[PDB]
Amino acid sequence: DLEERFERLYEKAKKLAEERGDERARRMIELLRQLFETVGDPRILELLELLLQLLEGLE
């Protein structure tokens, strides 16, 4: 399911952004969730995956 996969990814990305204190990333993650709930486009899932990879690259 696309929604269940997005929610798991959202919690993982939000958790990392909070650990880093990255307020800008936190707001991007919330916007991505709002857009995915509105549109449902799988490209929004890919965007969040790439944002998570970007944050993981900073660790």
Image: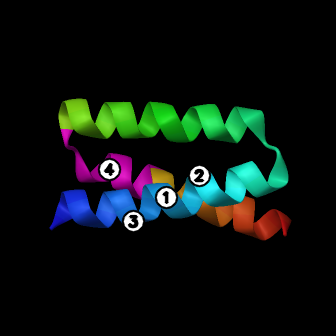
> Residue type at mark 2?
Lys
Q: Residue furthest left?
A: 1
For image coordinates 25% across by 53% down, the residue present is: 42
Q: CA distance from mark 3 to mark 1?
A: 5 Å
Magenta region, residue range: 40-47
**Residue 43 within the magenta-colored segment of the rendering:** yes
Question: Disc number at residue 8?
Answer: 3
> Residue type at mark 1?
Glu
Question: Are dots 3 and 2 in contact, CB under 8 Å?
Answer: no
Question: Are dots 3 and 4 in contact, CB under 8 Å?
Answer: no
Category of crowding for the residue at label 2, using alpha-carbon neighbours closer than 10 angstroms: few (below 14), some (14–19), many (at least 20): some
Q: CA distance from mark 4 to mark 2?
A: 19 Å
> Residue type at mark 3?
Arg
- Who is closer to the viewer here, 15 or 33? 15
Question: Are dots 3 and 1 in contact, CB under 8 Å?
Answer: yes
Question: Taking the image as drawn, is residue 49 in sight?
Answer: no
Quarter of the image with the N terminus is: bottom left
12 versus 27 height, above or below: below
| Secondary structure of the residue carrying numbered label 3 | helix
Location of mark 2 (residue): 14
Of pointers 3 and 2, the one earlier in the residue sequence: 3
Place of residue 10 in the rendered image (x, y in percent of width and height, measured from the top left): 46, 55
Category of crowding for the residue at label 3, using alpha-carbon neighbours closer than 10 angstroms: few (below 14), some (14–19), many (at least 20): few
The reply, left or right, for residue 52 in relation to residue 16 is left
